[PDB]
Amino acid sequence: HYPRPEGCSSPPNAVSVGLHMDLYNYPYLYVKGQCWNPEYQDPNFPRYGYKKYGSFGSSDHVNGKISWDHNEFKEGCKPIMARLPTAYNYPAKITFSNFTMVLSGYFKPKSTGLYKFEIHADDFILFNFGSKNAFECCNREESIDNFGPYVAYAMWPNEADQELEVYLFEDSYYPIRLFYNNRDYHSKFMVGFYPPNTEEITYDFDGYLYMLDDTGNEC
Ligand SMILES: CC(=O)N[C@@H]1[C@@H](O)[C@H](O[C@@H]2O[C@H](CO)[C@H](O)[C@H](O)[C@H]2O)[C@@H](CO)O[C@H]1O
Ligand SMILES: [Ca+2]
Ligand SMILES: [Cl-]
């Protein structure tokens, strides 16, 4: 039985394009008995530990080509400044070597059918999906950390590749929450999907990602 998660409904004027992003500090234990912080492994971390170093940035309308694979860095145990893809509407360089990111909003299928998602993580990616898994319809800011058991849990090195299948409907916006951490050095945040009856994967979310107003009525 393919999973069939709950979605949301909204009048078009209450809909805007793209996801919300918040960026959080994630320090090294030390910079110039390993150097990187193992905190990200604690089970309380994705629920509330991820905020305890404070945040440093946010953006909105995050759309299109949101994945990356940064494997060019030469040095470990050291903060390295680099830019996010332009999909993030976030101009400043970040400590790509060590940071945490949460992306939330809604995935809207273009056709009713079965979707397969594929994620590849360095270091850590969590995938929550559905009004009863990610967050409440039209109440994203209040319920953002009330997510359920993960639909996918990818951690480098040993659990770094994951996939999942969900059956989805044209007329519904599905709450979606993507948690990413880099503890150190190289950074990979790859979230792709296969639409229904489609053999080739895509990493372009353009036309699929939306935000609804936080009215709180289930819309
Ligand atoms: C070339 C090499 O082996 N460099 C090592 C790093 O692998 C290692 O850091 C880890 O790198 C992996 C990717 O392979 C991953 O991104 C981890 O997050 C990261 O900690 C590092 C140990 O601190 O030493 C480098 O020299
Ligand atoms: Ca890493
Ligand atoms: Cl659900």
Image (cartoon, rainbow, N blue to C red):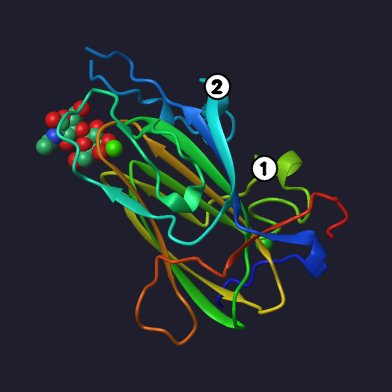
10 displayed left or right of 128: right
Closest to the camera, between mark 2 and mark 1, is 2
145 displayed left or right of 159: right
In primary-sequence order, the first of circles 2 and 1 is: 2
Mark number, residue 144: 1
Residue 198 spot, x, y in % from top left: 42, 84
The residue lying furthest to the bottom in this view is 197
Q: Nearer the viewer, residue 200 or 72?
A: 72
- Amino acid type at circle 2 is Gly
Residue 208 spot, x, y in % from top left: 57, 68
Residue picked out by circle 2: 54
Vertical side of 191 occupied by 79: above or below? above
At 52% across and 29% down in the image, what residue appears?
50
At 34% across and 52% down in the image, what residue appears?
68
Distance from disc 2 to disc 1, alpha carbons, whole Å, reads 17 Å
Q: Quadrant of the N terminus?
A: bottom right
- Amino acid type at circle 1 is Ile
Vertical side of 1 occupied by 153: above or below? above
